Amino acid sequence: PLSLLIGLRFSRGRRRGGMVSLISVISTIGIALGVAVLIVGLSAMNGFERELNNRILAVVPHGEIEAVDQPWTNWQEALDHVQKVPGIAAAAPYINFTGLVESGANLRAIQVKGVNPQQEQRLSALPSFVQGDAWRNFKAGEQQIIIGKGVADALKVKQGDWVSIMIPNSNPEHKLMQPKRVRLHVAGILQLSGQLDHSFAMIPLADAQQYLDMGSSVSGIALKMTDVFNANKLVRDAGEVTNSYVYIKSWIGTYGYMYRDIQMIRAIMYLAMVLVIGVACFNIVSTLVMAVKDKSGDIAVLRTLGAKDGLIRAIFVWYGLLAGLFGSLCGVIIGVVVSLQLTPIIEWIEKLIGHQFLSSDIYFIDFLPSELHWLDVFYVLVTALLLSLLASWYPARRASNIDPARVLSGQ
Amino acid sequence: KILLQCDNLCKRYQEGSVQTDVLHNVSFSVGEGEMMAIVGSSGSGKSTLLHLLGGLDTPTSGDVIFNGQPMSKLSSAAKAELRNQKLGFIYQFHHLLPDFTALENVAMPLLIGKKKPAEINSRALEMLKAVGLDHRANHRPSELSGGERQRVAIARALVNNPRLVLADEPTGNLDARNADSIFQLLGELNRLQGTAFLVVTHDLQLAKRMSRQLEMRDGRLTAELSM
Amino acid sequence: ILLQCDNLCKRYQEGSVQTDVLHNVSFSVGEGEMMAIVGSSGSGKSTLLHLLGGLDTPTSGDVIFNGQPMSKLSSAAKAELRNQKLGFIYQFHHLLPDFTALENVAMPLLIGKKKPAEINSRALEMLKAVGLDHRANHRPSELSGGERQRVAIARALVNNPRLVLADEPTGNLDARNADSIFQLLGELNRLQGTAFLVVTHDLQLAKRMSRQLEMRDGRLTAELSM
Amino acid sequence: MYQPVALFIGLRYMRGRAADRFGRFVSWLSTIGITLGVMALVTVLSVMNGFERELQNNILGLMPQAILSSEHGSLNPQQLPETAVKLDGVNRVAPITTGDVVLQSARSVAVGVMLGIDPAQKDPLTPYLVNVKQTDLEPGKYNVILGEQLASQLGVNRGDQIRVMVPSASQFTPMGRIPSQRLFNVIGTFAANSEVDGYEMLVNIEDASRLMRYPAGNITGWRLWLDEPLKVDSLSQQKLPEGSKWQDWRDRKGELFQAVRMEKNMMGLLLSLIVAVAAFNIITSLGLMVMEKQGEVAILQTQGLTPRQIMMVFMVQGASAGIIGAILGAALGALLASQLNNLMPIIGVLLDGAALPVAIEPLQVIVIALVAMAIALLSTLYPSWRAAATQPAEALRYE
Ligand SMILES: [Mg+2]
Ligand SMILES: [Mg+2]
């Protein structure tokens, strides 16, 4: 094929020996670098959302349907049949009250929680890996209670002992009924990031039998928004499935000024990624257009020799296709390698110390890479190949259009 | 009996500084199988004229008719059609593809016509031997000396047997050897093949080989050669 | 003595074949002496004259100027030389494209930092000498084929060099500028003690230099026997 | 014209032939790239600085940030005078008795923390108080101020007094460590726009001391305002001369600290990507330009110009291009940074971040421009020397 031969010869060096010109190799390297940086940035960005609703948002409840009239309003039959709407698929009930731990140690105040055994795993992500495996199977009878690294740490014992919290101030009504349920041992302990281990305690559901709470009707909970961001204020025109008495409590926006940080960070992320894309595209386009303009002289000779538009188009199409293909292959390989094996690159300059990028980051990840390939690398490769072909094509058409003798003399 | 046709072919270059006129109402004709020679002083406007004759510079207030059809008339595809089988243009300060050796450069009109591998090679070498630099068929223009590249350009022009051959000082960078020999070559071409020639040259000893040597006179081509 | 060649040989080989050019070149150009070189295309005239200057490294020879070889000169020393003693002209003459004819002619002087006024006056001096004052405002692109050659000649001779090397100074021009520029060089030599060594193909006026040599694929034959 | 040859040649090359549209905007691609890189870097840095300032002030500013004390309490002279209390940052000294407490209420039992401030001195929360005499606040039988998120909503509301408990107290050992408790009176309700409301309350000075252990007149420590609470790790790692334990806000809002640390780290990674790509473009474009003009270099060298002067010829052009690019990029980046609040028609509906910008001209902006200058100078320096060594005849042949 004539076009391929001419393109290859144009992409050849100025001197015998090396079969690669400086400009072609340079454009290849630029395209590869752009593709690699785009891949890395997109992978980190996607990992951001992958981790956000996995270790910092799942633990916090996504909503609440608490009302001032539980019986038959928020507690019709077993519960409000909020499962009808397809937004969520695990409602479960929810009972909350406060108490104190009595162990002859640093007393702490805990807002305890009620959780149903063989349940609460479809609801939130608080159930986490811990030595106390099969703990839920041991949760029953309203006797044993599970705490975090809170009052357990404050007290000088762990699961190895059986010290009871002895809630002394369980007063649902202001009058001091104070039913002191004592000898509630703990056999499992959980750990969470940072704080709020000080105010977590697991009580089997339907604990009202002995805690003097009224009946089996509790506050309840719902609205486990899977697409929390897209579900933001999505309860508008919805949520009537609950048929509660008073306006339900809000979604995770109730603990505001952290969701604000989340949204602001996401905005800055989008801005930075847009800047990356623009810079890389500009670099690639500038290099390709400069090279093609540098190769404008021979186009006039070909046109005056009788070359048609098709051959001129095909020559630079092949040139750009070759450059883009090789650069995209190299960039894809390097970027995939980096993204898949970036976090495992822990600098051993200081033995498990410092690294200048890891400090006080436990239960989170120093970096956050996630390679959602076969749907994102394809876009980058297609965009690179396009940009390359368009940059190759545009100046070639202009040079061919110009009177051949005119450009041979002027440029 | 007509190949070239000029009707007041005027031109002027002006980028916004001054009006630098070149030509004033050029008009002549080159008969089928007719030779002509152009003479004049530097700066007259010969090269610009011959560029206008082809479809390689837009005339200002004139037109050129080839085989009863103007040049701006031809579409881009039609002009590409024409340049392969009817144009034998040679370039002053001749420009060659630098990454292609002499053989490929000579063969390019045929490759563009897609003649044949074997025919193309044989005929490129045909014309190269005609010009007479067989021992530089493997040298790129960079490695070629000053004159052999000019002969390569001539061979490329005449490889495809064009009907008309426009030239810009085909033999001005060469000794008498290649000047005289290449005039012999063109002379046989015309009387063996019905090809016309129109060559601009400064060597007045052989300028009259074309006969009817015109004189470019800073606009209009004076019939005589009275300086 | 101005030029001195001792078996100035050369050869180009990129790894394909040994393409010899010259075989034991040796001659001299006397102070204020003209010479002309003749031969067939491909002989190696341009390569020879490039070797004469410090613009191509000889393989197995040397060139001595004013009793000091060219490779002897340091880079600064060669830059020193090229401003006041070299009047080299280029085949397929190359000019700065973004600089008009006047500035191109004035560049040797600007590099010498003569004066604003002197530089302008003398650039125009030499431009009028060659006779293209009408195209003193045109860049090389806008200039035609011959006026750029005359601009190159003027740039070569603007600074009054001791020796003037040329590569077909008048081969792209009609008899007008050929004869007139030979007249110009002729006055230059006998008004000013400047020697000339010009390669040309026009044999009518090649003998103006006198002692016309004949480059013959290595060694410059003293006779013009073809 | 100009006496210096290098300056004239560089300027003329920078101007270019300008065939149709300034070389179809191909001649100034170097300046265009410098501008784009500088603009992007400036915008990113300004927005990150604004984010850090927002986190420092609008959230962590109101709440306590650091406390020092001794084992279970201080001594009569506050365990120390003001001397040897200032270590780093802008530290303001103010006694405090922070301690978690249980605010039992008739409507609903709730828990929260408090601050033992004195009426004499101001605090972040003093201007927010409404319908109350903060300045004239005597103990008044343990008077307190709190509300607008706890008393007003899910509380005993203003007035009617409220319960306050301190679990950390050993009053009567025989039973289950009965804490120290007493009824407190409400005289106001602070209105706050941060998390302070609903989790924090104000108490008179010395009332927490009387209620809690250790002698009256002492405190639980001293507030220490920090100039860089974002990077409070360095302060915590350092041990103050007195040996007092360093308490910090990270003990409560650890999730936010970890999240901001990770976000800053990965944003630095993105900035590194930006810098690498931009610098690659600079080197590539300027080097290819210098290599492209080798024929002109050869023509120039044969007529008196030394290898050391052509280097200046190219460095002049490089410096001019870098200057134009850096100035344009700085201007455009400053404008874009101080134009990000608006231009959010539909994205702002769900993403109300506003991209809080902070254009810190003094240092961050200038350093980027200087780095670009140096990079351009070196990139024009090396290839110029490489091309100045080739023999002119060899260069003019391939040309
Ligand atoms: Mg001409
Ligand atoms: Mg030559």
Image (cartoon, coloured by chain):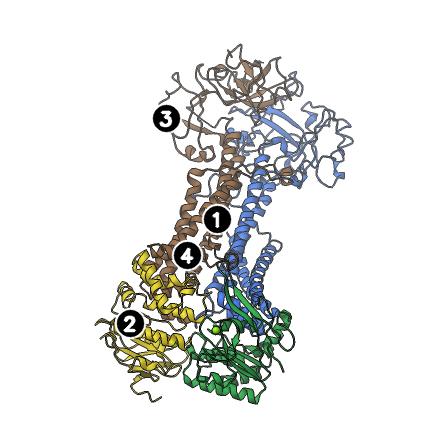
Chain colours: A blue, B green, C yellow, D brown
Quadrant of the image for the C terminus of chain C?
bottom left
Mark 1 lies on residue: D35
Q: Name the mark on residue D12.
A: 4
Q: In the rendered structure, which amino acid carries the disc numbered 4?
A: Arg
Please, is residue D92 above or below residue A407 in the view? above
Cα distance, mark 2 to mark 4? 33 Å
| SS type, badge 1 | helix
Cα distance, mark 1 to mark 4? 21 Å
Q: Cβ of disc 3 within 8 Å of ligand 2?
A: no
| SS type, badge 2 | helix
Cα distance, mark 3 to mark 2? 96 Å
Chain identifier of the residue bearing label 2 in the image: C
Q: Are marks 3 and 2 on the same chain?
A: no
| SS type, badge 4 | helix
Cα distance, mark 2 to mark 1? 54 Å
Give x and y (percent) for residue A114: 66, 31
Give x and y (percent) for residue C117: 32, 57
Q: In the rendered structure, which amino acid carries the disc numbered 2?
A: Leu
- Of D180 and D279, the residue lying toward us: D279
Chain identifier of the residue bearing label 3 in the image: D
Which sits earlier in the primary sequence, circle 3 or circle 1? 1
Q: Circle 2: is it few (<14), some (14-19), or many (20+) Cα within 10 Å?
A: some
> Is residue A330 at all visible to an observer of this figure?
no
| Mark closer to the observer (3, 1) | 1
Q: Circle 4: is it few (<14), some (14-19), or many (20+) Cα within 10 Å?
A: some
Task: Tell which quarter ligand 2 is in.
Answer: bottom left
Q: In the rendered structure, which amino acid carries the disc numbered 1?
A: Thr
Mark 3 lies on residue: D242
Q: Name the mark on residue C188.
A: 2
- Of A271 and A98, the residue lying toward us: A271
| Residue A71 located left or right of residue C207 | right
Give x and y (percent) for residue C224: 33, 87
